[PDB]
Amino acid sequence: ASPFRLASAGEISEVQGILRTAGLLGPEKRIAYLGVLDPARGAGSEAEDRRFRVFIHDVSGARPQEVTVSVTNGTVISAVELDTAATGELPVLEEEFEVVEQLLATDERWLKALAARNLDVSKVRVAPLSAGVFEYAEERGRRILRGLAFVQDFPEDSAWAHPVDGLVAYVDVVSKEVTRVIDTGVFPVPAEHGNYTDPELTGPLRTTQKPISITQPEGPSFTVTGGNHIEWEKWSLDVGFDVREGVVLHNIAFRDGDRLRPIINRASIAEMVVPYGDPSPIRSWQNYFDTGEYLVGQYANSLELGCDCLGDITYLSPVISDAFGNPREIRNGICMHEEDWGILAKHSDLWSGINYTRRNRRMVISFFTTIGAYDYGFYWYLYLDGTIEFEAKATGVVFTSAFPEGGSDNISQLAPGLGAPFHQHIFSARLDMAIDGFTNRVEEEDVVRQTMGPGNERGNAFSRKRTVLTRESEAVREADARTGRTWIISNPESKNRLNEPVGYKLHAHNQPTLLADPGSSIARRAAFATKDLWVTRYADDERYPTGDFVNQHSGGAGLPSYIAQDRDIDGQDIVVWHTFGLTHFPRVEDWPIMPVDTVGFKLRPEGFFDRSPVLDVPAN
Amino acid sequence: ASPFRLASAGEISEVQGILRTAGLLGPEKRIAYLGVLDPARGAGSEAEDRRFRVFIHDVSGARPQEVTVSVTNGTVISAVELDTAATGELPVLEEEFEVVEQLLATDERWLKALAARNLDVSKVRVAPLSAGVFEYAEERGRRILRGLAFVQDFPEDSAWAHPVDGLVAYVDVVSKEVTRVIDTGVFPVPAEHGNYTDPELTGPLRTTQKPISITQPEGPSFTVTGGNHIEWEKWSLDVGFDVREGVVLHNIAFRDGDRLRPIINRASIAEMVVPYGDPSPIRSWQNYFDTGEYLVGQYANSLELGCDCLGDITYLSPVISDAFGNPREIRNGICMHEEDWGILAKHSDLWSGINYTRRNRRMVISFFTTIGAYDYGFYWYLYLDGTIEFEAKATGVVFTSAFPEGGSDNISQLAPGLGAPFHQHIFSARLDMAIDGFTNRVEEEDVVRQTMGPGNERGNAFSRKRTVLTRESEAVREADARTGRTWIISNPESKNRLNEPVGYKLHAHNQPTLLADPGSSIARRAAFATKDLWVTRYADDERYPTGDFVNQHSGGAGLPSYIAQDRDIDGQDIVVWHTFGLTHFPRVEDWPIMPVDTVGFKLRPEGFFDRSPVLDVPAN
Ligand SMILES: [Cu+2]
Ligand SMILES: [Cu+2]
């Protein structure tokens, strides 16, 4: 019955059929994106109409389309041809990954470059990399991938150990042409392997680790109903999955006595971009929009009990489309479990004699994805005390280059002759807020230092200030760690027992935002990443901070275009977009496979409750 | 055997005997501090000489002494009479706390103030708080505590719910005189109780939480030898305990192949200060130095299996002195265990076909202390990958006031009429560095943005810069979150296989530092807390950032005096002092008992190893 249920295989098959019947899915067509649409505001509630949105590519050069279908009624709601030079190219297809290597393997410029370096073409892998928009007028409206080479000495070899620097190719994947091969000169190809399962490199495996057994003898404390509806320690939510965003949380609410109180209507990672900071022309174009260009959900891993998710795990197995509209299950793609989280609250009171300790726990909803060299874990946490947190875990293998003779200001050395270009991994969390319902506002809260003098004669006082963000033109905010800056989302029409608007406070990690020059292509295409916190008025067509079609879009799409409407956000239906990321200067320790590093954010109740919400937790 | 072993009951008794034999510990003497000293630099130097340092108070009003004893040799090494008006009072004696309420109960000014508020003196608890240094000239050379009153309605009542605002008293705890009673006028005493074990306030306890069982069927992976020497997953260290600092970690080192490589010689929390930001005269003096004034270690909790420390726990039970020099055990005061820590490293490689996942774990060493309303957990972590981390967990009951009828810029409201003055909890971690031995230096590393132009035509480049801190004058540093500022400790004489000095990088949380006006008493007394990072040259007598005697002590000692020496720190035996803290504007959710909030820091290897140090971890 839930309108927030996961897509079923049969709904995907029904989309396929509706498309093919309407003449929209001929043999030259490929589905680049397919997803369920969320219910509209003020449903309502009823006539449910399950709608799916689809992006259709044409491998013969015809114009692509965006198409919305109703699976409930068996109809095409809309179908629109796209002018890609205007609104952007469609996401990279998985079937295009191989095509760059194949086209290059019979190109005489490419063969010449390899022969100069004494590289067997059979051994040369080519990473299929997004192109962006630079100086090349011929690319506008064409679907281009760029290719960087890596040598694989044998089938189980890690090619990332052996980058071929000084060489890059550009290909048109529709016309099957190689438009450019650029060879700026020969760099040694690093020779050490990076095969982290070779005993020669690992040494003897430790035998010192004794097992840690995590079990739940009565099963888990959460319940899953309707496929994806979770109830756990007062929390209620629905776990969605979209092929672009991955795991999406819906209807996050907390049962406070008699009332189910909404907090967040929709939480997702709406974009994630990896800009590179090496000004070599071999790589200076490189910015991977893992979410917007590649679609992270579609590459979600199947997660293995005991290895990936430890304890008493409940899995979801979302269904997506392949390029032809057939459903495909991602078996065990989502892990759900509850974890112990140490001490929740503790006090040993001398006067009363009462010694009190309670433990904390968190509900975890996670998935893991792989985009080329990169692997990312996305984790959402709900705590007993009302805190909501997101954490990204970045691992995989470093995307490598040569290490230049005489060093580099933009590349670090991992192994002899093996470089790691500097880069960032920057995320955007889109939080469609619903603090006690939809009438919300955001304040920026700074600590305020006070001067010693009258009213503060000992010079000890300090305070804080809150500034309401009233319109979108005022709602593009930056961090200020030194003044303890946070942002509070409140409902001005819902007051706690002390007569203050109920709120939640966003605590950021205050990591650096996008470092690129503000006149750069990437600063224009990933404008969201240049600032920490954006607030918009909700609109059903404002989904991603980079717009709908990120691939080879010229710039300005998404948030800077939304914010330019200058809408009222003071007690309205609003969306917070928080930028957060890692700035990576890769270490020797990151090679030949990187230990996890993390980044995230959290939101804590701020006078949302009338007292602690965990007084009813029993002693352990 | 090990000179870093915990003090034994026999050693403490023997110090008592030595002091007695020397004429230093007659019946009017009290031990305000006793601890074992670390071995001197250079131990090739011959056998053990276990030395103890003692601060001896005299209840008859004679001057106190600082004494160092050799328990090995049965000797007094040094004994000096202190002039406390100059160099500071001794730490507060546990026995002095009760004195404040006792003396006030028969003081006619106090009784008049209570009668004005219709309070029964038998029901009035008095929090006995450190006095600091303000304008009261009669206090100079005297041991003063200040008292703030709270009503306890019955023996098991939480008195913190019922502050008595407008009243404060000052007491000389040696002469047993009430020096001042200040009554600025009656405030309503908040009436709502805060009894978080009362069913009326908790409601029915949850029955929803199913057990999480954490076990180690083959026992733990670490070994404990010599009472306190830990070996775990390549790590080696000794776990000390000092009544002032609490848990202290010694000789932190990592076994890399055949070589035991030092990293940190000594890690501790060398001070913590809790400044209050309410300019009322009732509280504007309020700042406690839990470590330096109270001695956090002495108030360490006994930790109970299953609620404090969950899993397969190995306890230490440190021994300290009582006020007479008799040994007293803190049973189960230190928890040691290893925890699963999610994914360590993961990559699914398209080209090779190899899918690889490994799990992480951390070793945890922890203790929990209570002083008055506050309860703090101090946690040290060692990870498989070489990361070292500290976390403080703040909980307890909020220290309350009245909430003024017209609101307040410096106090938040918790419950009707009940206020929570703004304050901070600020720690200093003293890290006596030994990165591959003692020849170390610190660099400040900032991200460097680059301008689009020649050499960077696409405007994508970014870099970083490192600035060596060469002398102590230049080594007092502040955070810059926006430029990703970190500090690298390296050994300029020990290079990795890529010919770069081995290092560790300190990652701070970049929270606000001390907020008080720089002209305040607290800004002088807690000068360390005004800046994020200090580096000194190692010296035997430079232990605490506030000096040896913090109680009622003005500026003049500690870090600003040390740094004046302007010593060479560029490839020398050096000590990093990191300030980090929480700034607390208490919420309604923090009442009537507060959920844990955290703050800390970590250090990660930075070209310390020649490649990832966890390639030898097996599949789970
Ligand atoms: Cu990276
Ligand atoms: Cu606090």
Image (cartoon, coloured by chain):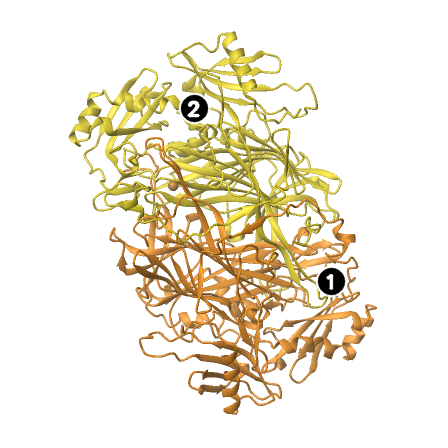
Chain colours: A yellow, B orange
Residue placed at 24% from the left, 35% from the top?
Answer: A165
Residue under numbered circle 2: A91
Residue at mark 2 to residue at mark 1: CA–CA distance: 61 Å
Helix, strand or loop at label 1? It is: loop
Q: Is residue A364 visible?
A: no
Looking at the rendering, which quadrant does residue A196 occupy?
A: top left
Kindly identify which numbered label has been placed on residue B610.
none
Residue placed at 28% from the left, 42% from the top?
Answer: A419
Please give the chain letter of the residue carrying mark 2.
Answer: A
Q: Locate the C terminus of chain B by quadrant.
A: top left
Residue A433 at what x, y percent from top left?
61, 36
Please give the chain letter of the residue carrying mark 1.
Answer: B
Residue B134 at what x, y percent from top left?
60, 73
Residue under numbered circle 1: B158
Residue B450 at what x, y percent from top left?
34, 42
Q: Locate the N terminus of chain B by quadrant.
A: bottom left
Q: Which amino acid does the dot numbered 1 rest on?
A: Ser
Q: Is residue A27 above or below residue A329?
A: above
**Left or right of residue B12, residue A287 in this image:** left
Helix, strand or loop at label 2? It is: loop
Q: Nearer the viewer, residue B234 or B116?
A: B234
Q: Is residue B482 above or below residue B220?
A: above
Residue B472 at what x, y percent from top left?
37, 67
- For label 2, the crowd category at 10 Å Cα-Cα, with few meaning under 14, some 14 to 19 and many 20 or more, is many
Q: Which amino acid does the dot numbered 2 rest on?
A: Pro
**Left or right of residue B252, residue A608 in this image:** right
User: In terms of image quarters, where does ligand 2 lie?
Assistant: bottom right
